[PDB]
Length: 23
Length: 24
Length: 22
Image 1 (cartoon, rainbow over the protein chains, first blue to last red):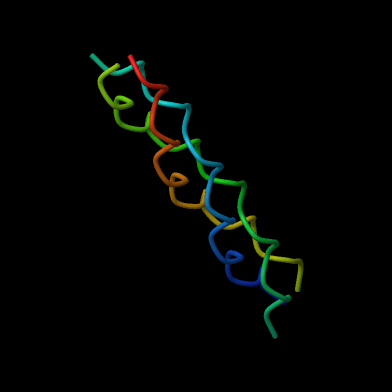
Image 2: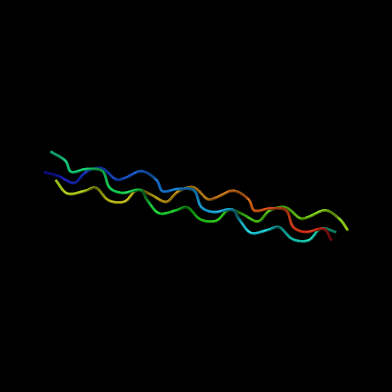
């Protein structure tokens, strides 16, 4: 038997870093 | 007959920085 | 048959939170 299909995409990455201080 | 599907892939990367905060 | 390979990476996560007040 041949290999199965690839699994599905993994989960989304975490939130990004906080933005910078305001003006 | 094909084997079973592979596992889920790795997590994606972190998102981009948030926006600047408000002026002081 | 053997198992398939791992899937691709997930999408990037969302933008982080706003920075602090200036």
